[PDB]
Every structure is written in structure tokens, then in C-alpha cells.
Image 1 (cartoon, each protein chain N blue to C red):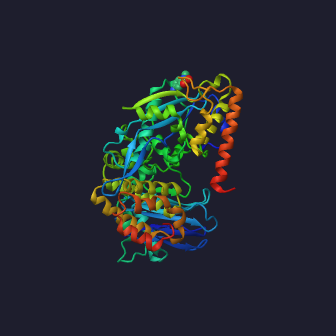
Image 2 (image 1 turned 30 degrees about the vertical axis):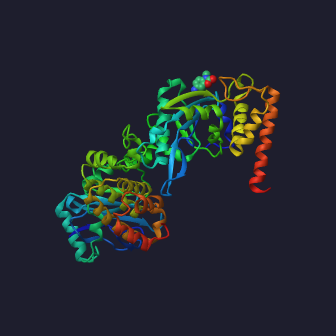
Image 3 (image 1 turned 120 degrees about the vertical axis):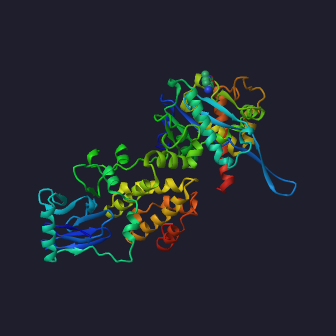
Length: 300
Length: 237
Ligand SMILES: Cn1c(=O)oc2cc(N)ccc21
């Protein structure tokens, strides 16, 4: 169990860690979060009491170093930083714990939600989507645009998701125009799985990271990317059976975890109705279909 | 964007563009079988690809053989249309290739777009107009060449005959849509109007009768009256 201390909390802010969140008052004596489960990625994220715009946050993995938070009054936000001095860091953490000024990552032992939502997400892959290689953690926010969004401006701050476009040469073999547009199996399996992602665990990991970025930051281009990756699978006649079964679990926990009041902008009517009811894979998502009908029958 | 009443004059500017109409590509008769069930039999069809500026009709004839052993024919019709239109553009010298292609039915957009991926600078547009090009098979000579064909075949016709020697493209296109609109709403009366006077003949290399200017006015007037009457009948106004 690892710790992320905070130097101070000088401004009122709602702090999130994974699917949990805590309200923190201006200059309240908050000095970090402890008992963070090791073995998964995590995200710590912020929304200032004064500006409900710009949700922002940091992906990290505690095995990659000792990380802490410090408010920067020039740039006006909570920044993640790395402490390289192991002993200076154990010292801060121990002293803060002794004074009991740290909240406890509040995991119910029966709960596999965070695992289920990050099964395939790997910190090394995140850092390739969010390129900033001086840091071992990754900053995302509400307003960052994707590479594909930029093609239709500042590349250093972009989400370098894998570009998927159903009406492109990459997706359509000459001479199989109608075939490949109606049955995307060759874009999925040959182009994307074998060619670019190499295996389905990287595909699934990008899908999961996209969803989480849409949920926690309302990042609109992440939501687009998440829908695109679902639709490519659902629109393929030929999908490995191991992938369909896992997809059904993956989507189930995403729909399960989504705030009820956000289903209107985060859920794309066309994609979901096509995947669950018209696509090749209409019958292969029983768990995702049952939870979608019992929780959001309006959208459908 | 979409083509509509407002941007209508754009058809006649000097940017090359083609209309594509797919209505007559896949044509069937419906009949009963020995056991009483219903069956379709396909007849030859065609793609109606027209430059509204010159009046050049690239009439691609769709032989029934293309359907042999295929399923979901009405969906395939749209792809076969897109394939043939794309092959026509590739066959044309660069200076002749269109800058726009305007599809009369929106279902053609994705098939054409996918077939034209090699032509990123050709814009594929829908339209809000209710153009009468389905009535093209009411033009005797076009219907005849389609019906007689024994193989796939492209046939080139000027749908304006020689009108452009005397009138503008704008006027020519409006005459053409008036004639086709009439043929669509009441073929029998429309055709009666065009051939009544046996002294007005159709040139061998033409589709319509050789009316003088004043006779076209009388004709155009008779076609208007036809269209308006049929509306009253349809709706009881
Ligand atoms: C010169 N010309 C004509 O009058 O009718 C044509 C049709 C086609 N497609 C190509 C050329 C012509």
C-alpha cells in the first residue's frame, strides 16, 4: 500500500482518486492519500470550488516512483511531482501519517470495480498517448484535444489516441470497398489488432483509458475515441471469441460506473443502438445489454 | 453542402459537376409462382449520370447478369452504382473529371464516398431537390437501348439535343426537368403532347422533337397545365 502526500491545500477543491472523491476546504490541513492499492494504475484529479470548468488530473503508478502534490500559485493548480530522495520521502509520509492528516483510499474488499475498469491499462501505454517524457505520470484535462480532432492545434498537449476512421483508405481495401465498409473485420483484425495494437490487451487498454478520461474529465475527444473502438468491434462479423466475452465485461463495468446524470453527453445514441441491436455482435453483449436496458432505456 | 433552391444557379457555372441518379439501376417485375408465392424477375437497368451544364448523359447500362447469385440486391445496387461512377471518373482525363458529384438519393453518399476515396478533392453532395430523373426510362430511345442490351454497355447521349445552340444551360435544364416532371406524373398524356403533330419529327441523333422556338413555348405551356391538373386530382384542391 502506497502513499501520495500533499504539501498543502491552499484552495477549496474537490479531490478525486479513482472513483472516490473528497471535498477539501481552503487551507484545510489535508496532506495526502494513503493505502493506495499497488498493482494498478491510478488517477488523482481536481475540480476547483471556484471554477467548475477544467477538471484536471494525473495518471500514475506508485511502483514507478514516489509522487506528491503541491499547489502552484503562479500557474494556479495542484501539480504532481516526483521526489527522488527516498529517505526524505518516507520521512514526510511517516510524519504526516503519525499526525493522521491523510485520508485512506477507501476500498471495500468485495469490490473489483477499479480493477475491472483498468484491467488492460498499462502506464507505459498511457505515456505514449500523453507524451511528456520528463515525467513518469501523465496530466490530462477537460479541454485537451486529440490527434484526430486536430486534423479536422498545439501538438505537445494532445491525446495521441490511435486514429480510427471508417471512410479512409486505411480501413478500405481497394476492390473490397463494399465488403470492408459493411464488415470491418479486416480493419479490426489485420490493420488494428495485428498491425498497430499487436494484441487485444493494448486495444482494450486504450479503450479503457479513453472511457476513463471521458468520465473523469468530460474529455469530449476521449468519448469519441471510446465509441469508435466499440463500434469497430461491434461492426466486425469476425471477432475472436475471447475478445467478445471480455468486451461484454469491460463495457458492463463502464456503464455500471458512469454517473447517472451524465448519460446524455457521454453516451452516443447511434453507436449503442447499432452495437446492441443491429450489429454483427448484437447477441454477444448480454451483460452490457441487460444493464443498458434496466438503467438507460430512454436513450435506446 | 446539400444542394437546394437557394444554390441552384451553381449547376450552371464553369465548375464541372455531375448528377448521379440510381433509381433505375435495379428494376424488377413482381409476379406469382406456381405455388402461389411472390417472386421478382429483374430487367435491365441503368445509371443516369448527367452534366447539367453541357447536357452529356453517361448512360451506364446495368445488365441483369450483374445480379446473378447475389443477395440484398437493393443494397448492392447502390455499391454497383458507386463502382461504375468511380470507374467513369477514372476513365476521364484529369481536366474532365468533376469537381462535384451530386447524388439524387442520400443513400448513395456512403457508397460513393467510399468508392471515391482515391479522389479526395471531388466533393460528394446530396440534394434537397425532388428531381424527376427516375422518368428517364420514359424517353423512348433511352428505354429502348437499355431493354435491348445483351451485355454491360455505356451509351453517351446529349439530353439537351441541340438546344444549347439557341438557349442557355439554365433554360435547358429547366425545360428538361419540366418534360421529365410531366412524364413522371402522367406519362400517357405527356407523350401524347410530344408526338401529337406527326409533322414534328425527332432527329435520328436526338431524343426529343425538333420544335421551333414558338412550338416549345406551346409545349412548355401544355406540360405545365398537365402537372398542375394532376396535383389537383392527387390532393383534391
Ligand atoms: C459532345 N457531346 C454531346 O453532345 O453529347 C455528349 C455526351 C457525352 N457523354 C460526351 C460528349 C458529348
